[PDB]
Length: 50
Length: 50
Image (cartoon, rainbow over all chains, first blue to last red):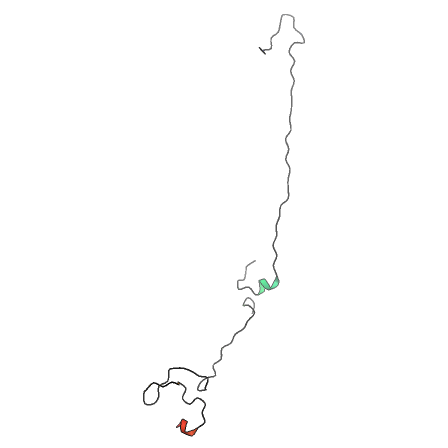
């Protein structure tokens, strides 16, 4: 039913068009930390805990 | 020194024949077992020493 067919004298019969689309992405930030004291390092039995 | 905690401990070897020397290894001159291992137990009585 939807085939493009011409005739003997054909003009302005079969017009077509085009389309484009877009994609996107984003970035985020992460992080974490820990704390300690001087006594914890100095008086601990295990050196090199750091 | 570092990495040893917060406590210091020391031995003491005073009791060579003092009263504080309490033990069960004693054997008298006859050969029998006796209660006190120390010979005199810091007693100045001549009878006890003899």
